[PDB]
Image (cartoon, grey):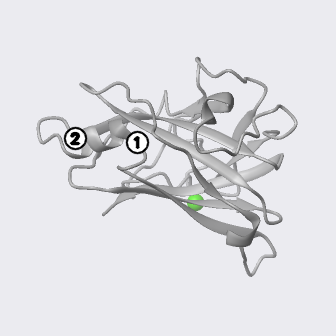
């Protein structure tokens, strides 16, 4: 049930338009019973733990669900960028692991070198009672991210694959953006 974005004026995934802004379970994901929806202006990913998408290691993210922006249809010039950051939100502190593969017209794939993890101790209580942690993936963690970010002839991201694992059946991602 993915939905194309309606407003991508911020230049990054803020999910403030009520859509999944292109994200849905990837066709090549080893796990499919994962719900991906927009809830309260964020991308809510449900049932990761119950469905076995709970590998939190640096190298075995391959066991987790793959979520990609197949119907995003927009693009982000990331020339010179070195970081892919995002907010991870949950009703309580959780453990979350994420690996990423940004994609471009001429650079369709690169095996991530490692997944980045945020643990319960990294989550901060917010005014609304929920918890939030910042997760950052660098060009040093994703070869294809580095390839696109350093290719002056094709530094435009046109899709992206995220490997997501967690011990929680309810987490959300928000403000997924590329920065220096
Ligand atoms: Ca948002």
Residue at disc 2, secondary structure: loop
Q: Residue drawn 40% across and 42% down?
A: 142
Q: Nearer the viewer, residue 72 or 7?
A: 72
Give the class, few, some or many, for how many residues have Cα within 10 Å of label 2's Cα (few <14, many ≥20): many
Left or right side of 70 for 27: right
- Quadrant of the rendered image containing residue 23: top right
Q: Quadrant of ligand 1?
A: bottom right
Q: What residue sits right under mark 2 in the picture? A: 155
Q: Residue drawn 11% across and 36% down?
A: 153
Q: Residue drawn 21% across and 55% down?
A: 80
- Quadrant of the rendered image containing residue 106: top left
Q: CA distance from mark 2 to mark 1?
A: 15 Å
Q: Residue drawn 46% across and 37% down?
A: 112
Measured as percent of width and height from the top left, residue 128 is found at 78, 76
From this view, report whether residue 68 is shown above or below residue 30.
Answer: below
Outermost residue on the left side: it is: 153
Residue 142 is labelled as 1
Left or right side of 2 for 102: left
Measured as percent of width and height from the top left, residue 160 is found at 45, 35
Left or right side of 44 for 2: left
Measured as percent of width and height from the top left, residue 62 is found at 61, 29
């Amino acid at each position: 049930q993915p939905t194309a974005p309606k407003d991508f004026s911020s230049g990054f995934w803020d999910f403030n338009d009520g859509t999944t802004q292109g994200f849905g379970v990837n066709p090549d994901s080893p796990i499919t019973a994962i719900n991906v929806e927009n809830a309260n202006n964020a991308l809510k990913i449900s049932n990761l733990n119950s469905k076995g998408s709970n590998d939190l290691s640096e190298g075995n993210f391959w066991a987790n669900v793959r979520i990609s922006a197949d119907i995003w249809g927009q693009s982000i010039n990331i020339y010179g960028d070195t970081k892919l950051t995002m907010d991870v939100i949950a009703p309580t502190p959780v453990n979350v692991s994420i690996a990423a593969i940004p994609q471009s017209s001429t650079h369709g794939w690169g095996n991530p070198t490692r997944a980045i993890r945020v643990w319960t101790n990294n989550f901060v209580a917010q005014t609304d009672g929920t918890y939030k942690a910042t997760l950052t993936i660098s060009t040093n963690d994703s070869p294809n991210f580095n390839t696109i970010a350093t290719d002056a002839a094709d530094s435009v991201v046109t899709n992206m694959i995220l490997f997501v694992g967690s011990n929680s059946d309810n987490i959300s991602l928000d403000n997924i953006k590329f920065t220096k």
